[PDB]
Length: 161
Ligand SMILES: CCc1nc(N)nc(N)c1OCCCOc1ccccc1CCC(=O)O
Image (cartoon, rainbow, N blue to C red; front, side, top):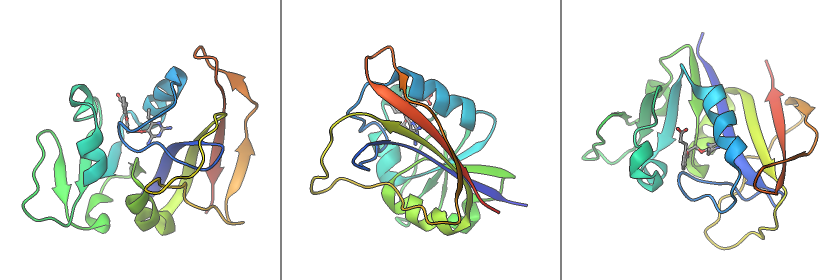
């Protein structure tokens, strides 16, 4: 049984953070992200891996896998694979970005963990949007919470079988 999960953070506009490209300051999201993914395999694209801050490259305490079709691409502290199917060896796999990988992994996913940030961030050219969730996703919607940054945010935990 190879369970796939997706986890991301988005503005209310749907615009998602990708790797180190995160425009909002929301410290609690990192603790939330770590609580979900710790002790599991995490899968990310090349562009996401590249945009990671060097201090968190690779991400500590987790089996890092990078999805790249470029055959010459290497990355210290992570396993590179050329197919998403090859990355889903573990019993629980979390896909952590970016947009292209989300879309590839979405048909396989049975869980989505979403952080929505209450911040004005219009869609602009080059921005990735959150994967669209259809009526198959069963979801518990969290209450707006105030971050110590001053921003409001809430947690969505979606699932399907
Ligand atoms: C916390 C950011 C984040 N939050 C959620 N809910 N989903 C993501 N896919 C996500 O991005 C994960 C990849 C980027 O991760 C970082 C980007 C900049 C600084 C620190 C981290 C995470 C470091 C860590 O997890 O130890």
